[PDB]
Image (cartoon, rainbow, N blue to C red):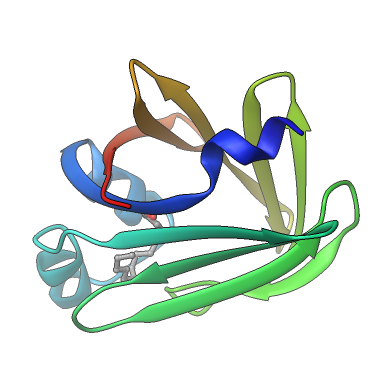
Length: 134
Ligand SMILES: CCCCCCCCCCCCCCCC(=O)O
């Protein structure tokens, strides 16, 4: 399964344009100040057809579980209540969130052994680079 290469624990080492991405979502200044300065850990697990993606940080934790291709309800780290779907498109794990007539896509792919997360909302595009910890 293509998901096997994503499994494990990943730690943020680099970020580009995250503040702009949060601004585009309406995250307030005080939260952006802290969120831009944290280095989250993302844990990706799979048991049968169910994938679980956990994001851990010193001040906020999220967890979602899903089957690929099946829409699910998600409450995001910034408290948006969204409709989500995740597909594995070739080698790219593509997570689409929809709410209030808006969308944002979170694409994860493996480049040179690192996990690259690209977040797009409107024209705000952010790249988050994660190194494999375990
Ligand atoms: C995940 C770090 C703390 C997040 C605090 C809430 C404000 C920003 C949330 C924006 C949507 C989720 C972004 C995830 C980024 C990532 O996984 O590197």
